[PDB]
Structures are given as structure tokens and as C-alpha cells.
Amino acid sequence: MKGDKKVIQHLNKILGNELIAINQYFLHSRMWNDWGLKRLGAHEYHESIDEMKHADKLIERILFLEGLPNLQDLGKLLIGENTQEMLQCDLNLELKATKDLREAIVHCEQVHDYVSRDLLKDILESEEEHIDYLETQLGLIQKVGLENYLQSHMHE
Amino acid sequence: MKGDKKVIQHLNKILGNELIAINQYFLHSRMWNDWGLKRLGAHEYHESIDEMKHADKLIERILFLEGLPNLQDLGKLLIGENTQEMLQCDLNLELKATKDLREAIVHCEQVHDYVSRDLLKDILESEEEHIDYLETQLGLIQKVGLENYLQSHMHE
Amino acid sequence: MKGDKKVIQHLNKILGNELIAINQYFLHSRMWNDWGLKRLGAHEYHESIDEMKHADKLIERILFLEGLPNLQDLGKLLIGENTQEMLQCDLNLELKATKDLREAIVHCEQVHDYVSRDLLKDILESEEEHIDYLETQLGLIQKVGLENYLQSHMHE
Amino acid sequence: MKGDKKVIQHLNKILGNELIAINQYFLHSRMWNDWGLKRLGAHEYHESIDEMKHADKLIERILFLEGLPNLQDLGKLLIGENTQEMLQCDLNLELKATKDLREAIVHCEQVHDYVSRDLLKDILESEEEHIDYLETQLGLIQKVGLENYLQSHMHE
Amino acid sequence: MKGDKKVIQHLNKILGNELIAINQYFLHSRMWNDWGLKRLGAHEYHESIDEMKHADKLIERILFLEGLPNLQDLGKLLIGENTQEMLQCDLNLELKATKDLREAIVHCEQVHDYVSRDLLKDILESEEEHIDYLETQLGLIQKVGLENYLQSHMHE
Amino acid sequence: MKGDKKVIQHLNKILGNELIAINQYFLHSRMWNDWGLKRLGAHEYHESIDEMKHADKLIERILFLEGLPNLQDLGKLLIGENTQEMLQCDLNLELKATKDLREAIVHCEQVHDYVSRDLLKDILESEEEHIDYLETQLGLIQKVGLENYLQSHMHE
Amino acid sequence: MKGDKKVIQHLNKILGNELIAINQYFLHSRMWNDWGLKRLGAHEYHESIDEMKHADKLIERILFLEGLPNLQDLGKLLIGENTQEMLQCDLNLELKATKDLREAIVHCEQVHDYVSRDLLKDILESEEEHIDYLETQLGLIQKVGLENYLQSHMHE
């Protein structure tokens, strides 16, 4: 079913953001596992897989709308080098992602693509849940101290 | 995540309406039970619990958006003295609640807080279901007569 | 069954104290959850629910005694800004609650309302259990240190 | 164990009241069954059995305290001729029973027979539950009408 | 169904005998339990319950026959002071009960109330079984001696 | 929670009585077992354990009330030399225990420590049950003879 | 079976040591529970119960040997005011207990009471296991720090 050109462009922009996140979260997960921080490693693995699920739905919607999913352009991964930096890098990425989701929803509404809007709203709910997790972890580091925070994430 | 100040004000206004409804429905429930109208008592108890679930979601959303949930201001409970009046009191409250929900959704849409809009839409769906129940009960009183209607609500 | 007017006034006073505690504990629970201190959040949620159960029994007793339960007057919530303050706010509220329960029991005994006395004694047992919990938590903060205490309350 | 002579007199007075109620409730139950009001008949049967359980506990306590249980004196049964009268006769008896229970509790407290007091308090709780039931039924007759009330008590 | 007036008088006389036995056996049971003769206590409790079942059937029959069951007149309880006396008191009562049952059966036969006769015959069979039990216990006291007889009735 | 000094003194006095009883009953149990009176030995062991449970509750209450439990002062054990004397020694101790419980309940009532009163009432119920057991055993020795009484307590 | 008088005296000395330990461990358990150090409380409770089992075996052996078990003399309880002191008080007591056990075993061997020796050796093995536990806990306080050690003993 032929979709709106600018809707497809927005969906590809969102997809691009998801693809950055998949790789950033996967690498952060394996860094945490290598360091023995297995609870963080496991949680971050699940974040990567969740982003994969959103990317899948976007690819499927773009193809239904007769557009070309762009999996070729990979933007800048924000790779941290210690736990605090990695969490902040994930948060910086998620805040860019939600800005782009809101702009995409505005356009879907304007052109009456209510099904694409609903998909993007579901993704936005997941991304806000991730922001909640990240803000909470950064706050816990302050409240319990970094050494205790890391200790609590050694064991699954 | 820093929310829109006016969104947070709207969410607190909705929360205030829920808090009235929780208490009004709980008292109505226990009045019906005291009178031996246990089917009405049980249904009204479930209505109170459902309002508690909505209030919980509003409180959680307000905190996520870095606002202060207001559980201190309790507005006017509309307490009936007999079954007909109690149902009409619940209906009067629900109609004010839906007006406020619609106004809050307008504002969430305007500032692109699509997740808050979706939460409020889910609450609005529940409130419209309650309106349907109340209108139906008031109509049944007219069709079957008050004595039969009360008889049908003695036993669970 | 027509109850003693002063007993009913005392039961409404107790009920008012419970209604403050329900809302104060519910808000504290959701604050702790927002901060990632989920063990505190869960325990405080259960404290709120327990207070709801006491309020229910008081409402039921008042109605049986042919009085009017007052769910309209909500007194001052004592909301802390950090864990130490929130626990102390809960403790300050519980100490006022037990003072009022003891005075109400004295009056029930004087007028031979032994069943209302038994209800209040059961509520008082629950409130003293909550005092024990609160004093214990405040003591643990001193014994293990604040950072360790909070660490031990991150995971349920 | 040698009990207080006046305590034993009070326990025998309570026992006498229970023995009236056992027989009154049993006869009312069988009258309702004969008329085909089987739900009333079953509930009233259970009321008779509950009074039997209280009488047993009183007989047991009297014997432990080295007194003579009096099962010989049977006071006046209050037998109605229709459902409304039967319910009111039960209520009239229950209100005499609670007056005597409260006076017995006062005396037990004054002579430090705290175990006898606790037994009497439990019986008083059961008698107040019966009062609630009876007041509720009389109220339902007014709210739903006699014909509907009786209809609702034909089948168990 | 309108019964014979004299049949109903006979049924009320039998019922009166049963009501004596219920209370006499119940008191004897609780006396034996107080003394630690729990096997006698349990057996005598079951005798009381069985008499209650006969009384129920008599009450039900009287009401079907459009008479008024008399639960108000309680005759003389025969209460013993030791095991031998208590068994003999029960036997003395049962022998009066069977005389009255036989006279009632004669009258039922004469007026062709064959269903009332059959009820009374079933009650008479139960009362003769009780006579057998009582005569047997009294004989055992002679054969094994009182101390052994009581020893054998300590434990259930 | 800071308790009343005299309440704590009373609870420590009760505790002291329990500690005597624990040891007296345990020794009596093991004497009966050594003599092959295993039913008495087992029953008396269970009495010792039940007293331990009461002592635990008193210790816990004293600590909650910010007092010092006294497990150091052990009063005079009343040890019999044969079954009759041992049972009477237990009864002599239980009668002093109930006097102290009643006096402690009075004081708890007067300072409004209704939760401590309820604990003591529960202990008093257990002590009166023990008195019933002991009086019953002494009476059975009279009724069945000492040799039969002991015979009946050889096998569990 | 007539035992050696000095063996019996040694067994009563051991028994006296056990009786101190039972009470000291029980009080320490309940102190740790009141402070919210429930893992220490539970472990120390089990230490008290285990000492009770040893005391029982000593009492049984003394009676078999035709001696009089002494449960009347209670020696000095060593009660700490904080966790470090309580552990050291338990250790001080256990070291005295093992000294007395060794002297008792010597005498049992000298008079050929090999069964009493075997009982005492089993008790000694249990006491050395307790010493191992206590020395280990005191070492852990040094290795992990007091605050972490207490944190690790909050939850069971």
C-alpha cells in the first residue's frame, strides 16, 4: 500500500536510531560481562534485544508502505569506557531518539497515517521506560555510592 | 525526565478527581453492604479498586516527569442517602471526570506528550465504561421498578 | 444497632488517622520505587494496603452503629524528601495514631462497647508492629550506614 | 479451679439466655421450612447451632470453675406467627442477651477473671453479628417489599 | 395436612421426653469430660445429638400435621453425681420414654396415622438400643469393677 | 518503643515464673520417661515446650519495649519424688503463676498497654488449661486408683 | 544402673554449662532479631536449640545412672551490648565449656565409663564446631568491616 514519502523517511530515521542503539547496547552488555558485572550485562543485553524488536516492526511497516528500509547507514555509537559513562551514553542516545519519535508522530498525524502513529507511540513508550531505568541507575550511583552500586551488579 | 509543567498540573487535577471517586465509591459500597444489598456493594467496591489503579498510574507518571503528586487536596464527596441518589451521585462525578480528561488530552497532544495522552485515553475508556454501567442501572430501575431492582442486588 | 455517640466520634478520629497514613505510605512507596529502592517501595505499599484494611473495618463498624463515616476530612500528610526523613515521618504519624487508639479504647471500655474495643486493640497491635519495623529501619541505618542500608533495599 | 461465685451466677444467666435462643431459633427454622422458605429455614438452623456452641463453652467453663451448670430453667420463648414477627422476636431476644453479656463482662473484669471475660467477649461478638443480620433483614423487607423478600428466601 | 388432635398431643409428649434427654445427656457428657473420662464424655455427647435428631423429626411431623410444637415445657432432668448414678439416671429416663412411645403407637394405629406410627417405631428402636448400651455398662461395672471400668473410659 | 517501667518489671516477673516451669516440667518429663511412664513423660515435655513459647513472646515484648529481659534469676524448682507429688508440685507452681499474671494484667490496663495485656491474657488462658489438666489427673488417681492411673500412662 | 558418683558430678557440671549457654544464646538471638539482624538471630536461635539437645542427653544419662540432674543452679550469663561483644561473650563461654568437657572425659576414661565418655566427646565436637563459627565471624568483621558484616546479617 503506497505510503507517504515523508512518513517513510521518518520511519527510516527512527530505524537508524534503533540500529545505533542495538549495537551500542550489545557492546556495553559484553563489556559489563567481561568486567564481571553480570547483572548489568544481562539487563543491557535485554535492552539490545528490545531495540531489535522495534527495528523489526519498523522494517515491516516500511516494506508494507512500499519503501526501502535503510539498514546501511549506521550513525555514531556512543561507547562509554566505565559504568557511569556507559549509562550516560545510553541516556544521551535515548533523549535523541525520543525527540525524533515525537517529530515523526506529528507528521503521521498530519497526513492521517494513524497506524504508523500508533506503532511509533508504542516505541516511544518503550523508550521512555528505558529513560526511567537509566535515570534511576544514575540516581542509585549517587545514593548508594559507586562501589556499592557495582557490587550489587556483580551477580545475576 | 523533565515533563511539561502544565501536563503535570493536568495529571494532578485528574489524580484529584480519582481520589474523590475512590472514597465516594468505597463509602457507597459499604453502605450497600450494611443494607444487605451485597451485589451492589461488591460492584461498587470493584469500582473503587479500579479508580485506585488509575490513581497509581497517574502518581507514577507524575514522579517520572519530576513532578510532585498531590494526594493532600481532597475535593467534595457526593454521597447519596438511597440507592437512586448514590448511583446519580456517581454519575455526576464521572461526567466531571471525563470533561477534565478530554481537556488534559488536548494539552498533552499540543506539547507532544504522547505517552501521557495514551495513559489518559486508557483512563477515559474506563470512565466511559463506568458511565455506561451507571446509566444502565438508572434505566433498569425505571424498567423493572425499584423494589425488583433492589431485590436483584441482595445476593452476590 | 444504635452506638454511643462518643464511640462513633472516636472511630471517625481513628479512621481519619488511617486515611492520612494510606496516602502518606502510598506516596512514599511510589517515591521509593521511582528512586530504584524497590524493597522499600514494596514494603511501604503493603503498609498502605494494611491501613486500608483497618479503615474498611472502621467504616463497617461505624455504619453498623448507625453513624456516618467521615472520609471527607483528610489531615496533613507528612511527606519526607529522602529515605531517613520519610521513615521518621511515618514514625511520627504512627505515634499519634497509637495515642488516639489508646484514648478510644478507654472510652469504649467506659461505655461497655467491648466489641469496638476488640477491633481497636487489633488495629493497635498492627500499628505497634509498624512502629517496630520503623524503629528497626532507623536503627539499621545507624548500624550499617546509610549507603549500605539503601543498597540492601534496591532489589526486592 | 474454684471460681468466683458471682461469676458462675453470671455464666449461668448467660447460659439460660442461650438455651432460650437455641429452642426459639430451632422452632423458627422448622416453621420457615414447613412454609417453603428454605433459605430462612437454613440460616435460622445455623443460628440455633451457633447458640449451641456458645452454651457448650459456658457449660464447660462453669464445670472447670467448680459450679453447677443449670440446664433446667428454661425462660420464655418468643415465637412469632409470620416472618416479620419471627425476625423481630429474635431481635428482641438478642438485645436482652447483649445487655446481660455486658453486665457479666463488667463483673468478670472487676474480680480479675480475665479468661471468663474473653469467652463472654467472643460470645458478644457473635450476638452482635446476629443483631446485624436481623436488622438487615427487617430493613430489606422495607426496601424490597415483603413479597419479594419472601420470594428471595424460598430457595437455598 | 390436618392431623388427629390426640396424635399431636402424643407427639408433643414424646418431644418433651426427648428435650429432657438432650439436656441430661449433654450435661452428663460435659461432666465426664471435666473428670477426664473422655470416652464416656464422647459417647454421651453422641447420645445427646441422636436425641436432637429425633426431636427434629417430631417437630417437623407436628408442623406438617398443623399442630404447634411445644419446646417451652422442660421436665425434670435426672442428674447424677458419679458415673454409676449418671448411667442409672439415663436408664430411668429411657424406660419412661419407651412406655410413652408404646402408648403413642397404640393411638396412631387406632386412628390410622400409619406414618406417625412408623416414625415413633424408628425412635423406639433407637431408645431400645440406648437401653441396651446402658444395661451393658452397668453390667460391666459389676464384671470388671468400678476402677477398671472408669480406667477403660479415660481415653477415647 | 519506650514501655512503662513497671510493665517491664511485671513482664520480667512473669518470665521468671515461666523459666522455673520450663525446667521443672522438663525434669519431671525425663523422670517419668526414666520410670517407663512414657505417656506422662511426653505430655510433660509438651508442657515444657509450651512454656518456652510463652517465655519467647515475653522476651520479644520486653525488648520491643526497650527493657532488659532477665534470664539470669532462676527461682525455686518444685521437684516431686513420685507421680502424685510431681503433679501437685506442677499445680502449686501454676497457681502462683496465675496470681502474678492477674496482677500484671491490672497494671497493663492502667497504663493503657493493651497489647501487653492481650499477650498476658493469652498466656493466662494457657496456664488455666494446664491447671485443668493437673486437677483432672489428680482426680483420676482418686477415681481409678494409683496403680491403674500409672498403668494407663506407661504407653504413649 | 548405679553410676560413679564423680562421673555424675562431672555430668551435672557440664549440664550447668549448657544451661548458661542455652539462655545466653537465646537472649542474644532475640536481641539480634529486635535490631533487624535476622540472619544472626536465626543462627543464634539454632545454637540455643542445639545446646538444649545436649542438655537433654545429659539429664537422661544422669537419671539412667541414678543421679539427680541439677537444673536449679544457673551460672553467670555473659551478655554483650553489641554484635562484636556478643560474639566474644559466646566464645568466652565455649572455651570454658571445652575445658570442663576435657576434664570430664579424663575421669570417665579412668573409671571405665566409656558410654559417658562417648556422649561427652559428641558434645565436645559440637562445641568445637561452635568455636569455629565464632572465630570465623570475628575474623569476617575484620576482613569485610563491621558495617558490611552487619549488612550481610540483616536478611535471612
Image (cartoon, coloured by chain):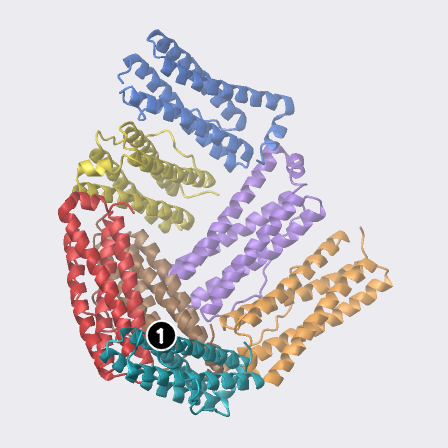
Chain colours: A cyan, B red, C brown, D yellow, E blue, F purple, G orange
Q: Where on the picture, by quarter, is residue G126?
A: bottom right
Q: Does D98 appear above or below G41?
A: above
Hey, which residue is sitting farthest top in the picture?
Answer: E110
Image-based side of B126 in relation to A48, left or right: left
Question: On the image, numbered disc 1 is attached to which residue?
Answer: A64
Residue type at numbered disc 1: Phe
Q: Does A50 appear above or below C19?
A: below
Residue A7 placement (x, y as % from top left): 30, 81
Q: Quadrant of the C terminus of chain G?
A: bottom right
Kind of element beneath mark 1: helix
Q: Where on the picture, by quarter, is residue B45?
A: bottom left
Q: Does E144 appear above or below A130?
A: above
Q: Residue at (54%, 25%) from the top-left corner?
A: E84
Residue C54 placement (x, y as % from top left): 33, 60
Q: Nearer the viewer, residue C76 or D153?
A: D153
Residue B58 placement (x, y as % from top left): 29, 73
The residue carrying pointer 1 sits among few (fewer than 14), some (14 to 19) or many (20 or more) residues within 10 Å by Cα, namely few
Q: Nearer the viewer, residue G93 or E103?
A: E103
Is residue A29 something that shows in the picture? yes
Question: How many marks overall?
Answer: 1
Image-based side of C112 in relation to D6, left or right: left
Q: Does E45 appear above or below C83?
A: above
Residue A102 placement (x, y as % from top left): 29, 83
Q: Nearer the viewer, residue A82 or C77?
A: A82
